[PDB]
Structure formats: C-alpha cells, structure tokens
Image (cartoon, helix red, strand yellow):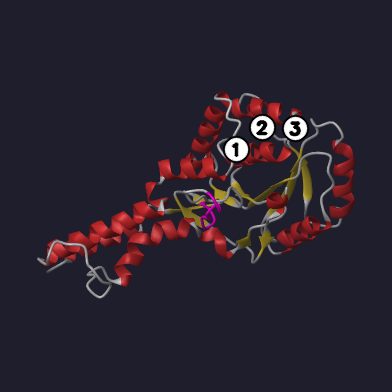
Amino acid sequence: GSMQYFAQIVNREENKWPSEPINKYIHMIWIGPKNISDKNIRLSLQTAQKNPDYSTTIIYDSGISGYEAARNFMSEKFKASKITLVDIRNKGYFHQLQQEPSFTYYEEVIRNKKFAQASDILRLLVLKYEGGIYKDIDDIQIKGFGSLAFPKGIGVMREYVPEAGKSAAFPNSPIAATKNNPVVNKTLELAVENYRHGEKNVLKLAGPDVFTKALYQEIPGMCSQVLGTQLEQFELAKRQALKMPLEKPKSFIDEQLTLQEKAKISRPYKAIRGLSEYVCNGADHSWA
Ligand SMILES: [Cl-]
C-alpha cells in the first residue's frame, strides 16, 4: 500500500475523542426582583414545547430580598406549562455549593445586586453538579435538541468577535456539558482566580472571555488559528509522504490536502460547536 499510514492519521483525528451523551436538563436562570419580560416568557414556553423529552427549569434565588414579587409573577405565567421554578437554595446539593469557592463571590455579587454577573457563576455550578444544557431566557430555541452527544462532553456555540477586541469568544450560553465536565471546572477555577485578584473588568471574571480561555486550555484545537496550523502541518506531512516540494502551497489548486481530509481533521472541533443549529442567541444583555 501507499499513503495508508497518512490516511490512518487523518482517520485517527476524526474520532480522537468519543462523543459523550448529555443529560436531558435545560437549566435557565432568572434571579432578582425584576419581573421577567413578556418576550422571555414566550421564549421560555417555546423552549419547553420544542423539547418535550427535556425537563426545563427556571432557577431563581430566595436569598435576594424582594424575590417573591418576581417569583410570584413567574408562577402565574408558567403554572400551566412544563416550566417548573426551582429555588437554588432548595437544590439537593446546596450544602455542597456553600463549600464552593465561587459561591462566596456569588453571594458577594448578589449582595451588590449584580445579578447578571452572578448568573455567569451559577450556570457553571449547576452544570458541574447536574450537567445538561444551560440556556438563557433571551436565547431563541430554533429546533429541539433531541439526544445530544459531544466530543469531550462539551457543546458550545460558534464564537463571535467583539467589535473592539482582538480575540474571538465563545458565548457562555447556551452550554451543553456532561456532569462535572473539565471545561466547566477550569472555567470555575479561572473565575475564582479573577475574583481573588479583584478583577474590576467584567469581561475577565466569569463571562465568555473566561469560558473561552478555559476551553482553549482543555481543548487547544478550539482556537481557529491552532486548528488552521494543524491543517498546514498535515499539508506539509502529505507532501513529504508524496515526495513533493516541502513548501506551503501558494494557491489553492496546489494544496495536496483534499477537502475531505480537511473535514476529517476538523470533525471534532466542528461537532463541539453543534449547539448553533439548535439555538439563536439573544441580545438582552447587550441592551443592558
Ligand atoms: Cl503507507
């Protein structure tokens, strides 16, 4: 045979990480005394309707003064649906959450009434113990999830580019993850280090930029430049096995790596971005 070893390397990269199933829980958070908007109520109902095999819950907090007025508003609006409000205090692992370093900052942030900044922390704690899919009340459910399985047990959206930043960022919503996922844990570790270091920058706390940085440490290929570098290395490796000029191709027609070979190498990192065909992101936090 010829090129059978090179074709074996390409096939190894396609299934290097087996896809792990995701628990069928849709976690959504709405904490504070502000009432949920009419749009977010309709999107939440649409979320539960499009996922009858998922149990959809909206997580509120009873440790915030004035929470009853907003919680009473949600129950009357969701009493005839599959949306079941669950208090984070009444969780079956709340005593373990109190022993988490991030929960002290969660308590410290809700006291300052920075509810959106606190939601970035709680969503990772819920995915740590229970797992499943976190989604925000503003995220639009395009189609139902069904049985989802992701390489490394982690599913995210396509990364966006901040209009002034220099690095892309994966949104921290929606996030699909297995129970006690390494990417979720590393995001919590970086979040604790940022809060320990008094990071006044809201981006360098528990938001998408921190979730992205933790995703790159566990799965370095998620960085577009890293995967692109890996494709250029296979291009040179194929030329060496072909006994062709060991050089980077000048034009596209001179590339030896076929499109099918590029797709095989990129298969794991495409699947991790699989949540983009199920959910459309909302911009409620943008207007805030
Ligand atoms: Cl060979």
Q: How many discs mark residues in the rendered view?
A: 3
Whether residue 141 is situated above or below residue 183 in the rendered picture = below
Whether residue 237 is situated above or below residue 126 in the rendered picture = below
Q: Residue at x 63, y 37 (%)?
A: 121
Looking at the rendering, the stretch of residues picked out in magenta corresponds to 155-164
CA–CA distance between discs 3 and 2?
A: 9 Å
Q: Which element is circle 2 on? A: loop
Mark 1 burial class by Cα count in 10 Å: few <14, some 14-19, many 20+: some
**156 within the magenta span:** yes
Q: Which element is circle 1 on? A: helix
Q: Indicate left or right for 243 with 105 as reference.
A: left
Q: Residue at x 36, y 66 (%)?
A: 263
Q: Residue at x 29, y 55 (%)?
A: 230
Residue 9 percent across, percent down from the top left:
24, 58
Mark 2 burial class by Cα count in 10 Å: few <14, some 14-19, many 20+: few
Q: Earlier in the sequence, mark 2 or mark 1?
A: 2
Report the residue marked by disc 3: 89
Whether residue 93 is situated above or below residue 271 in the rendered picture = above
Q: Indicate left or right for 58 with 263 as reference.
A: right
Q: Tell me if label 3 and label 2 are in contact, CB under 8 Å.
A: no
Report the residue marked by disc 1: 129
Quadrant of the rendered image containing residue 48: bottom right
